[PDB]
Amino acid sequence: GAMADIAHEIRTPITNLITQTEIALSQSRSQKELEDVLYSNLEELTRMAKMVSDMLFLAQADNNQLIPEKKMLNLADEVGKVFDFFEALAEDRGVELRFVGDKCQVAGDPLMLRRALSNLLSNALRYTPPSEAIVVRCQTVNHQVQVSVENPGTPIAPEHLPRLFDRFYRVAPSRQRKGEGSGIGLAIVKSIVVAHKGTVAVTSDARGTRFVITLPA
Amino acid sequence: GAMADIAHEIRTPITNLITQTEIALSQSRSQKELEDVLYSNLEELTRMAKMVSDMLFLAQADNNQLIPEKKMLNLADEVGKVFDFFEALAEDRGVELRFVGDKCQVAGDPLMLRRALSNLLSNALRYTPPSEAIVVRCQTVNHQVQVSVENPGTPIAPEHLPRLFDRFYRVAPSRQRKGEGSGIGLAIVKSIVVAHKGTVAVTSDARGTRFVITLPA
Image 1: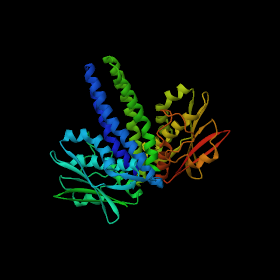
Image 2 (image 1 turned 45 degrees about the vertical axis):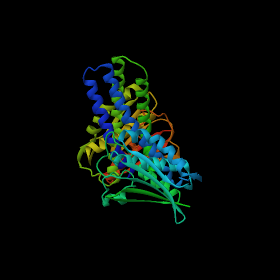
Image 3 (image 1 turned 90 degrees about the vertical axis):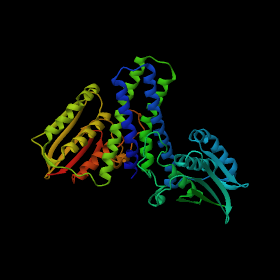
Image 4 (image 1 turned 60 degrees about the horizontal axis):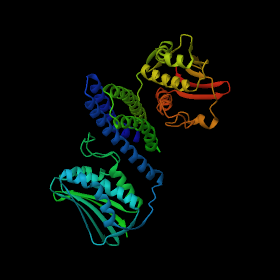
């Protein structure tokens, strides 16, 4: 349950902080060496606070109080707001962020949908090779809107596919240092999409990995 | 819900550490000042490490993996060990620790029963007025061993009595640091006792509050 899952998420960052602080204090360090330990500590603590924030959001969905406040959205507009916050991360990794859509529009909660799109982009940036593009595609199909986040990379093995949106599920034991993920980013995507009466789907093979949100239209 | 409760509990220590760290890094401070910050941090991280381990302990009970390794115990000796660790805390508050037993013996897991007794003593020390006594009484009643932890102080209102051992249940949205316990100390007491095929009970009125563990004998 949550007790074991959350404790096992935090046990190792806590352990690292003690370990590195204990090491730092065992020897006489310069003033800036000590500041670098603090900044290092702050980075880990910051990830922990993000995990806490994510958990409180997801908790709304349990208790069934995740209630989208919907209006007609221009998805080109909303994706662009998210790209602006990921442009530096993308440039560092050497990846293109690309939007594809032809006047694509949908009723939805923009706060929640930007959160879902952000979590899908954070996921894709973990796995996309340099000199490739992450593509966000939007289109209307059979009176629904499909929004897909597509990335080249190593395929996700079948055993993980139905598990990807589970709370604190991780494909590799990369429950890890300095990487990415609260551990419930994808669970948050699915909860937002289900609250919009939609579904999420993933396909993954040699041609790429595709996370597809289907929303009523 | 479960996740929300845990999120709220761990948030405060994370938030405090982040705040202290940020304050520390906001100005150019001495090598000595930064040492004192990191040492203080070390102390808080140590407390968070106790918190997570308690969570893992309770999760073990939840999964029905709390299996007591029982042997015949001299409870005067075990309570003695616990009093030794709480003596300075009690003295600071001006509270007497008193044990009452007449060759009291019971079959139990000593590490676990000491954990339960410590948690009850922590609880009592939150609420016992200065110049009063906390009494730990051990006796046999109807062929069972009863260990009671008794403290004077403000009665617990009836609505709280059946909730006292619930994880993260708080009688009062109290102070937010340190004297409080983990939020799951009393849940851990109940889990340990139930795993011993015992029960816990509480009575509370103007004459005092009594937490009683009953164990097979």
